[PDB]
Image (cartoon, rainbow over the protein chains, first blue to last red):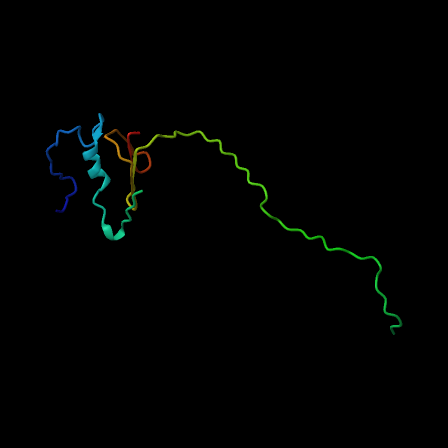
Amino acid sequence: ARRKWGQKTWSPTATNGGAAPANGVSAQEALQIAYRPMPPSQTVEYEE
Amino acid sequence: MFLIHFVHYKTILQKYTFKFKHIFLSIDKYNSLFFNISGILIWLNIIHINIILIKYSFFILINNFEYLIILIST
């Protein structure tokens, strides 16, 4: 899509703590924040 | 003209001077917040860094003072 200056398209809420839940984030929710969709041609991943 | 070949009796020794890094001291005394971190996600528009240590439950702190900084479980 392409955006216009001054015109925004409203989107519904997920109703889970807002965009960032201040009360906390579980392990399975933070697993998706962990393996966030970075472009893999320019991404290095590492675990120990 | 030159009649004699003479050398000087006083023998000089060249003082060998050299600068080496022999002492290793450093004044480590800062005033800053230091955190226990189970995850840190640094998002600036050029480089994104995601460092995750696993847990059952996390928290979230978010700093937008300089660049987006997301801290999991403080």
